[PDB]
Image (cartoon, helix red, strand yellow):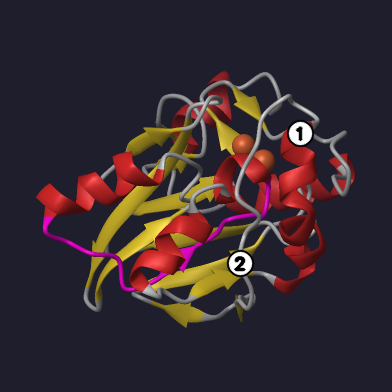
Amino acid sequence: VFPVTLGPLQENAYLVETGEGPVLIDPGDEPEKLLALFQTTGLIPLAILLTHAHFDHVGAVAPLVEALDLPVYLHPLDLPLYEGADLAARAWGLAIPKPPLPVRPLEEGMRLFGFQVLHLPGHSPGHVAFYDPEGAQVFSGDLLFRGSVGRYDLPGADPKALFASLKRLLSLPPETRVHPGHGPGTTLGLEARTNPFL
Ligand SMILES: [Fe+3]
Ligand SMILES: [Fe+3]
């Protein structure tokens, strides 16, 4: 697990090692920091996985793809966002290289790279979580934070959605390690009793 923090908004990209080996979750920005991270790691990612298509999570995809021809997995419901992520970036006074097409569709119940894909909308229409039971953990993007939860006013978000989606998450192993797209890690158990959103 190569937690690594990219981009002006400090998002949390992850290199994970599975049975089928290395994958990269949410290459947010700073390819070089990412490309150079591989220089040393030795582990090159067999595929880029996206929890959602928000610009702060997909800003490095273009570069990485044009350098290692990795396929890009994303839930189809986020395509529209994904395709418009670069303009979204400019709403923050920032800028990303428009994410490349095509992409391979993610899907509820789908198994890949040891992970078990859960569709958990709310923060966005195509937001998913990557559950690693062999890892005892979960890469849940902007869904769950240490003491907070994903925004629900960004275009495409929905509180009621985010809420049913969270309740789902919070019914897995309390001891499950949360790997969020921003800030310190945590656990479903910890958040259950501490988070002001629960
Ligand atoms: Fe987000
Ligand atoms: Fe984010």
Q: Is mark 1 within 8 Å of ligand 2?
A: no
**Pick the front one: 145 or 88:** 88
Q: Main secondary structure of the magenta part?
A: loop
* Picture residue at 35% right of the left edge, 75% below the top: 113
Q: Residues within 10 Å of mark 1 (few under 14, many from 20)?
A: few
- Range of magenta residues: 42-54
Q: Amino acid at mark 2?
A: Pro
- Residue to which mark 1 is pinned: 90
* Picture residue at 56% right of the left edge, 47% below the top: 59
Q: Image height check: is 106 above or below 58?
A: below
Helix, strand or loop for disc 2 = loop
Magenta stretch encompasses residue 43: yes
How far across and down, in percent of the image, does residue 170 sit?
58, 45
Q: Is residue 149 left or right of residue 124?
A: left
- Residue to which mark 2 is pinned: 100
Q: Amino acid at mark 1?
A: Arg
Q: Is residue 110 left or right of residue 21?
A: right
**Pick the front one: 68 or 76:** 68
Quadrant containing the C terminus in the rendered view: top right
Q: Residues within 10 Å of mark 2 (few under 14, many from 20)?
A: some
**Pick the front one: 66 or 193:** 66
**Residue 50 position by quadrant:** bottom right
Q: Image height check: is 151 above or below 112?
A: above
How far across and down, in percent of the image, does residue 151 sit?
76, 32
* Picture residue at 73% right of the left edge, 49% below the top: 85
Question: How many marks are shown on the rendered structure?
Answer: 2
